Amino acid sequence: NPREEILDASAELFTRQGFATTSTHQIADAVGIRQASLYYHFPSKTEIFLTLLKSTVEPSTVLAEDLSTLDAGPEMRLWAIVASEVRLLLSTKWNVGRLYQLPIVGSEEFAEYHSQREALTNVFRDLATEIVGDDPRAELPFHITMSVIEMRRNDGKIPSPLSADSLPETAIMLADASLAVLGAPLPADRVEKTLELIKQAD
Amino acid sequence: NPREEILDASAELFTRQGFATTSTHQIADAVGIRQASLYYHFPSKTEIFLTLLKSTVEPSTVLAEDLSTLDAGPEMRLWAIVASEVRLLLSTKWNVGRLYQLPIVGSEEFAEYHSQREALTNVFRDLATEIVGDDPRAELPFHITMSVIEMRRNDGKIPSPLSADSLPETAIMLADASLAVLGAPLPADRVEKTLELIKQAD
DNA sequence: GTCTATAGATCGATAGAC
DNA sequence: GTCTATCGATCTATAGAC
Image (cartoon, rainbow over all chains, first blue to last red; front, side, top):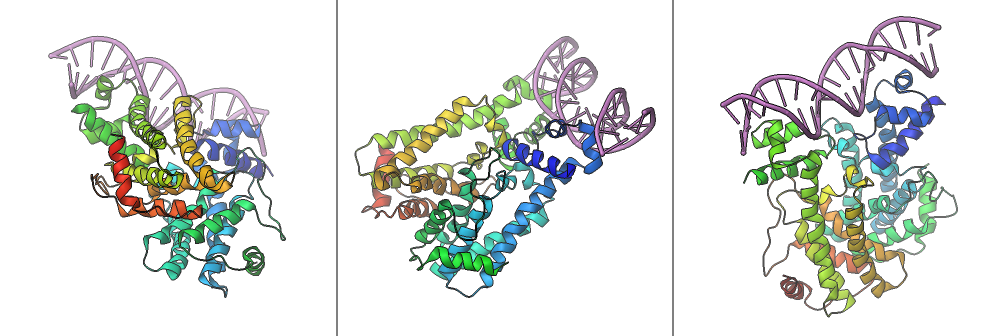
């Protein structure tokens, strides 16, 4: 409970200001306590950031790794993964997708989180190579997906909560743009297998 | 001469580590002097950052604003602006395109640089509306352009230096992808006409 | 579990010798 | 124009009272 208020206050501060510019004092004041009291619940300011980062990088990678196994066309699997990731990043209270873009993540310690983010890019890149071959356009579907980070709000209200029966329009547009840059036709009933394939991957 | 070595070392450190994590001592050690000696050539560490940022934001904004005036089709000007910007961002020794995405730019003091980049995004978005109307796809050409920042090297060697008669393959691909997400056909002789409009804007 | 107080260390920037 | 030396501010984390 008090651990949750610290992570929520840190999520807001880190996404808006970054890790280095945010101070433990600022985190404690948002909680309503004083700076030293944070260290009862967490060992270090870094550990708060790692907890938030680990709750964003790893569900994104296991979701894409689960949707690559399922039986569909490469265009269908790529369209589903792009739509699923955007729906992931549009379902959080804060724009936690920003946490990886922070300069501090470029530190040489995040080899654990670098491999998960390179594995996530490998899923995007490999499905695209299956569509258009050894073409530099294969690297575009992943950056088209992450561009939602620059579009969604960060005021504390969830842009599009998750639904079993619906998909956000931003997720559908970015998924259509991903197939478009590869010159691939859009599969029939994109949204209605993705909801089933998302239901498949638990 | 000494100002350029400080700016080059700061360009490397800021792009790779960010503004907050980089120390004036680290900048001075790359130049080969002591930390205090930096303040002979520059008033503050912030002023070093502003000089590098202003040498990237304003050539990007005046280039796009100059090519929007010229007489051509909206698809031709959008393809040209995307291709020209990518080659700009591929022509610097360091990946200075990263400097605006740093958390420190989000400060409420950078109101000059926020308005300059909102004009730059407006050029991309307005040309897209001329192509696809009031469609959320109008925001994709700019993010497709900026994705080159996540693709180019940052070791100190220029990925593709400038040429009067040629364009980098990455510049052509992102420009073809930008029109593709809008469902627009590519104009005849894209690469060979953009070279003329770049010669136009000096 | 929260507090006050402070250690310990870094950093930005200034002053003045040469 | 570069140097040594230092001030003052800010910050992470710890110690110990309660």
